[PDB]
Image (tube, one colour):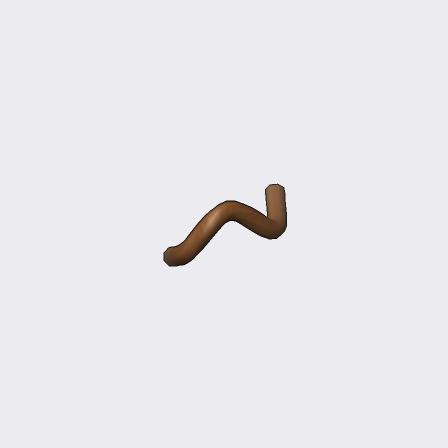
Length: 5
């Protein structure tokens, strides 16, 4: 995760 989707 991290904020790509």
